[PDB]
Length: 139
Ligand SMILES: Cc1nc2ccccc2n1CC(=O)N1CCC[C@H](C(N)=O)C1
Ligand SMILES: [Zn+2]
Image (cartoon, rainbow, N blue to C red; front, side, top):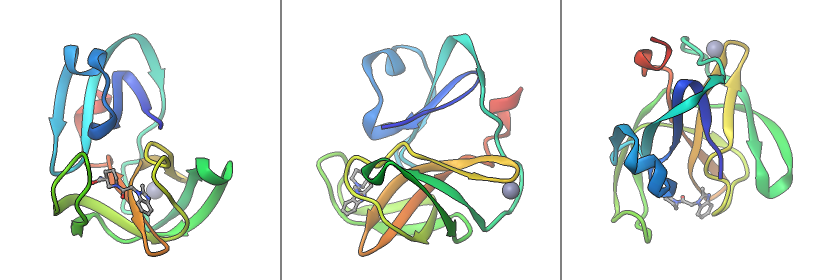
């Protein structure tokens, strides 16, 4: 689990969005596994606006933060699951690192702030859904 709280928005993995998230939907994208909903309280997370390829992510399955080198957001084939059929997820970044079902939601951060959240994994590789291009989250 996990979410990004910026201004009056909450960003979660689309496959984990709650009834409250859908009832207050701002934007969702199945191809990116992202959902954004509105909040009444103010969020203080800072979104990175950069092209960083290094950062640190939180891995709940190990209660530890790990420094990673990651790829530029792209279209990557993601194996079938109970939430989605086998498809190409867009705006996805891979890193060599630990993850397991339950780690989605952990934040990836660089020196500029929040880069994205855990969305995929397997084979000793962790995938992160990029959020840096969602310029509207700050305005
Ligand atoms: C996060 C993770 N690490 C894993 C390691 C090994 C095996 C599975 C692992 N998952 C879960 C996974 O990849 N899923 C399930 C939920 C929907 C995700 C999606 N964005 O399509 C795909
Ligand atoms: Zn950065």
